[PDB]
Image (cartoon, rainbow, N blue to C red):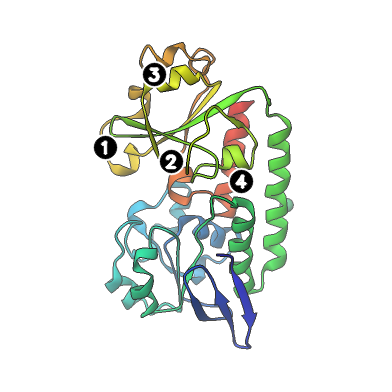
Amino acid sequence: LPISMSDEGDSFLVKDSLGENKIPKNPSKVVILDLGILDTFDALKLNDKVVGVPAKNLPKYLQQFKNKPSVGGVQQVDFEAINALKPDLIIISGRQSKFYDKLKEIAPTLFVGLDNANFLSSFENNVLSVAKLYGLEKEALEKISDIKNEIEKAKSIVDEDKKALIILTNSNKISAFGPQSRFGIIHDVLGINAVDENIKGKSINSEFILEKNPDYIFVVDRNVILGNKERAQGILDNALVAKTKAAQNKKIIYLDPEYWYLASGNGLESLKTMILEIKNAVK
Ligand SMILES: [Zn+2]
């Protein structure tokens, strides 16, 4: 899984989960398909190195990239746009690893997908590997070290005797998520305890939410990105959920899907912002 780099000379020899590539030092035409790593390009001030972004799903907090050429959205990738960009590096995560072999036949292709078993070290590893390509380890490391400092302050104020449920809404169905899921940060990094123990979505309904009776419900609404009419606020407005501690104490928290579901915490900007979003809610 983890990312290792050996300095040849003009270039690095980089091994990741999917394979090995000859990527040059200071690549100047980069296609980026992971949104978290695109916020990490912005943090380290490398906007001009980015030649193409997936503009279909481009979040509010990355609209400084709205006029980069589009190479698609996160599901469907435009090979003929990526192709005409003559990039020297393409960066992808899990949603594009389907196309690993075809993108590799165009350019060195770096996988930077997160490991939900080891979020912090795989996150730190992705950020540093990228900064290593441009010689910005120093700047990245102090930015990581800030994030770690904000984490410890978020933990301080966590009340250990309270439990949380994480759920995702889709059309009018609901799914539960736990530890080491794609949303596991809340449990694994910030240490908020889970109401239930269950494998890495899990289909549930409102009676399940009540017999569990969480103090917090963190809600990720997929409907927005999917372009559906319905919303989580509508779905969770029933008399079963109204009886939970979380409802009675107004601790049903709608998390920003652009952060939690699209970038998934895989950037310097997004992770810091997500830690603060939880901090202010469990406060
Ligand atoms: Zn600082």
Mark 2 belongs to which amino acid?
Pro
| Residue at image mark 1 | 228
When the figure is inspected, residue 49 is found, relative to residue 41, above or below; the finding is: below
Q: Quadrant of the C terminus?
A: top right
Q: CA distance from mark 4 to mark 2?
A: 15 Å
| Mark identifier at residue 207 | 3
Mark 4 belongs to which amino acid?
Lys
Q: CA distance from mark 2 to mark 1?
A: 14 Å
| Residue at image mark 4 | 272
Looking at marks 3 and 4 on the same chain, the residue that comes earlier in the sequence is marked by 3
When the figure is inspected, residue 119 is found, relative to residue 208, above or below; the finding is: below
Contact flag, marks 1 and 4 (Cβ < 8 Å) = no
Q: CA distance from mark 1 to mark 4?
A: 29 Å
Left or right: residue 259 compared with residue 271 = left
Determine the secondary structure under disc 3. Answer: helix
Looking at marks 1 and 4 on the same chain, the residue that comes earlier in the sequence is marked by 1
Left or right: residue 191 compared with residue 245 = right
Q: Nearer the viewer, residue 263 or 200?
A: 200
When the figure is inspected, residue 25 is found, relative to residue 171, above or below; the finding is: below
Looking at marks 4 and 2 on the same chain, the residue that comes earlier in the sequence is marked by 2
| Mark identifier at residue 257 | 2
Q: CA distance from mark 3 to mark 4?
A: 34 Å
| Mark identifier at residue 94 | none
